[PDB]
Image: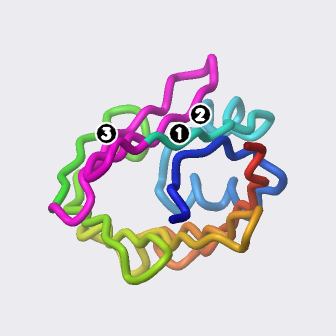
Amino acid sequence: PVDFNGYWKMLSNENFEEYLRALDVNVALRKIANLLKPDKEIVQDGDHMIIRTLSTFRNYIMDFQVGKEFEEDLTGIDDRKCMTTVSWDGDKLQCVQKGEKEGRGWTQWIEGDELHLEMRAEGVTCKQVFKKVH
């Protein structure tokens, strides 16, 4: 298999400031948030997946369940609740952030050694290419 379990370093980061502006978060958040770049790390035992991100600035840790509906509560980032479903179309991953907005949701996929993810929010598609450093 492809076993998502990996170490993904951040190479790029596009339209990330407008993405925070689009989600209407605070100015102090965007001041600190830009100069930073979090290193992602994926862990998956089987039908349980834990998405670990490690920054000394507010740990962004998420847990998930594949094929089973997910719910989420945020109080530090654009404090919204959405209904999210993580599934496997084929050999990729997708998430439908079912809530407000016209364009909410992320798209995942693997291009061998690099991720080609896309993140939208109110119509602003930002992208972040990572480099699997396994």
Quarter occupied by residue 70: bottom left
**Looking at the picture, how far across and down is residue 130, in whole percent?**
74, 55
Task: In this rendered view, identify the residue nearer to me: 49 or 15.
Answer: 49
Determine the secondary structure under disc 1.
loop
Q: Is residue 20 left or right of residue 65?
A: right
Q: Is residue 98 left or right of residue 78?
A: left
**Looking at the picture, how far across and down is residue 39, in whole percent?**
68, 37
* Residue 59 falls within the magenta-colored stretch: yes
How busy is the neighbourhood of tag 1: few (under 14 within 10 Å), some, or many (20 plus)? few
Amino acid at pointer 3: Leu
Spatial CA span between label 1 and label 2? 5 Å
Residue lying at the far top of the rendered structure: 56
Q: Is residue 11 left or right of residue 66?
A: right
> Which residue sits at x=43%, y=32%?
61
> Which residue sits at x=26%, y=53%?
47
How busy is the neighbourhood of tag 2: few (under 14 within 10 Å), some, or many (20 plus)? few
Q: Is residue 44 left or right of residue 7?
A: left
Q: Mark 1 touching mark 3, by CB under 8 A? A: no
Name the residue that disc number 3 marks. Answer: 74
> Which residue sits at x=55%, y=34%?
53
Spatial CA span between label 1 and label 3? 14 Å
Range drawn in magenta: 44-68
Q: Is residue 55 above or below residue 8?
A: above
Amino acid at pointer 2: Leu
* Residue 49 falls within the magenta-colored stretch: yes
Task: In this rendered view, identify the residue nearer to me: 49 or 23.
Answer: 49
Amino acid at pointer 1: Asn
Task: In this rendered view, identify the residue nearer to me: 105 or 69.
Answer: 69
Q: Mark 1 touching mark 2, by CB under 8 A? A: yes
**Looking at the picture, how far across and down is residue 106, in whole percent?**
48, 68
How busy is the neighbourhood of tag 3: few (under 14 within 10 Å), some, or many (20 plus)? few
Name the residue that disc number 2 marks. Answer: 29
